[PDB]
Length: 49
Length: 49
Image 1: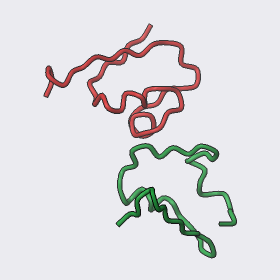
Image 2: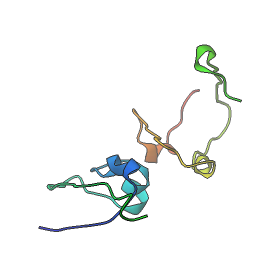
Image 3: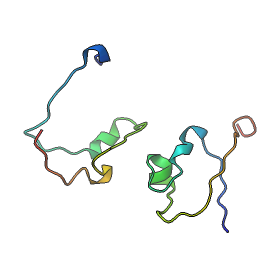
Image 4: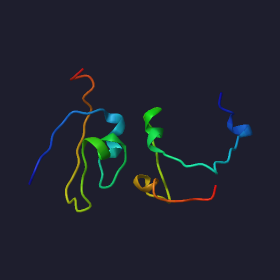
């Protein structure tokens, strides 16, 4: 198994998907059409700001 | 000013060559969702109006 960890704004979390839109899914990261895994997120505004 | 939804406006576009890349120069698009056409391939199709 793999792992990619990062803190990023939570208003664009929907961009994390195969063939999604927005900067996260176009110009900053991308997932292929063969992704078989999971995505996890949790609030980090208070801890890191 | 932008007319409100209760009285919507409408303008046609034709008789001109169009380039949507300069469209990115105005402001970052929040959604930019294209339903029937691939957004990447908006620059190779010839339309009527």
